[PDB]
Length: 369
Ligand SMILES: O=c1ccn([C@@H]2O[C@H](COP(=O)(O)OP(=O)(O)O)[C@@H](O)[C@H]2O)c(=O)[nH]1
Image (cartoon, rainbow, N blue to C red; front, top):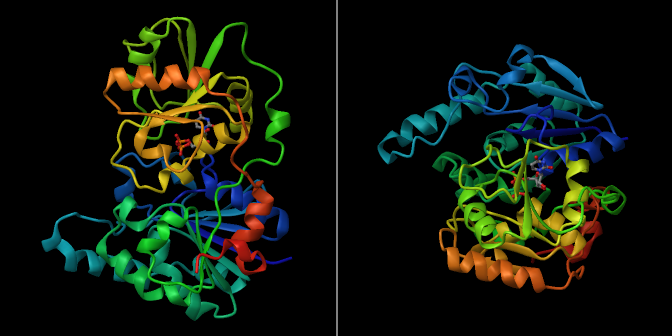
């Protein structure tokens, strides 16, 4: 039993699990498992961080589902000011941040056999991990491209600097490789799915009729549903965890649900006629076609999908539209309604995914070079 440390600006305790949470669940099955949460400060708090409900636990270890969680709270955290004249202040703050890890981080690094750094702020601690524990296998999990996150220049330069020294760079999408300045240690590992997705998919939340589903708040475009619901009165749109309420534009054929536990979303997904990834913008990375979690979930079931053209990507059963263009929304839906359900996409479970995250060389198909 190996001991894992995950560094991320997620916190493991926050209710909507992201990819790193699912991986972390798998790590917790394999060995000790600590999740150290970064980029959280007093500043964070006065800006609406998802982690604020955890604030009274800050800087202490809390056990959550077999994971040791630590939300690091500093007074300020370094960030992209987005003003290129403020750069040397940024560099200063990132250097300062990186130079002042808490003892708990250092201890956890020392205790770890494997340290996973999620793309983002965690980059600032890769070198530190190498110094603290050169025996630790250093796994960078690229949930997102650095440029997409729009990290400070410091983090890009630092990532570029340290990236070759990482044991594993596990890209969610090969499309991320262009901006990763390393080769021999760069691997492709999607997105897992729950090993029991098919069992979770039964029963059925839906009565008779045609049901379409959207799950998730990422770039949530209510206007999609404004148009789609009006244009398709015979379709019931199930809008789950959109991060917002009932937009006044929604037709009565839209059902708006609060955030739903992942396992419970699945029946809504499996038994839908088609799913929707209503990203409000096409100013999105090319990799989002691969990295979108909801689209992966639809894909698992072969659920035809309506999504912006920019995230259709190299996939069947995705019908692109232009956000804000009613005609294209209607055309895409019209096609989705008639698309057959076929499981085109191979979806490894989270356990098999985590295996390849940790030892991609044992699975040579993951190699990008
Ligand atoms: O109330 C919710 C909202 C989101 N999700 C899931 O959370 C993941 C991420 O959703 P988000 O929109 O934030 O990102 P995306 O899927 O579009 O990448 C997706 O698999 C959703 O299916 C969920 O289970 N319940």
